[PDB]
Length: 241
Ligand SMILES: [Zn+2]
Image (cartoon, rainbow, N blue to C red; front, side, top):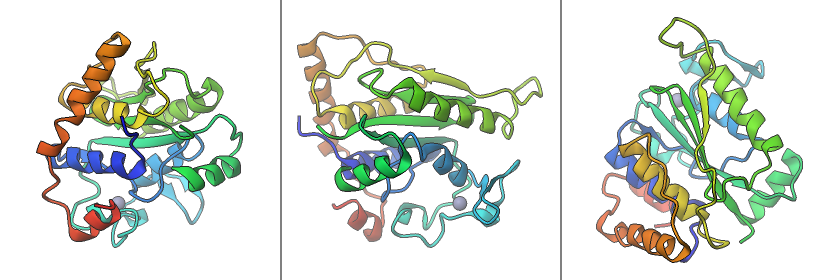
């Protein structure tokens, strides 16, 4: 398997967004990291005021950075950026980075050095789903505060059925590694999102090594029958297509 880089992963997200109109695809230019994912989610839900540098208690559409932005969001130029329900973020990690400056410098240079995972925010199900094909590649000390802080902040905005502001549930769905090589993480998380969007209770099967390879190959072999057809020339250019 040729690995999938940020552009290949983003291409699959755009492909999925053509099938699932509720799916928000984040920046095509900057992947998220454990240090930046909460800020990215809050800004995409219009819950962040860059002028006070403050989290908002309710969305404020005047804070929107999705319009007229053809570097990060050419695919949102003609959408209502508010109208989405499922937000899926490719998340880049390297274990040698211990602060945002280190993680960012490393990411900017590279995004077998990269590891890719996925954070999904599902507003309808009040859940934050974290997918890592290697299960625990990211130290809990780094990923858990981010997942739980997002869950807590979004619970205060999207109430539960009891009328309470309970945190969204966090689901770290892979307990046993499914990935068998050093390079296929981007393909795995793309397959996961594909299946999740048809069934949010989906969890990939535990497979032998050879079976997993055949499984991934089967997924890859669908891709040529699934061209992107609704994207603007600007979006296609950013995707490197
Ligand atoms: Zn917006």
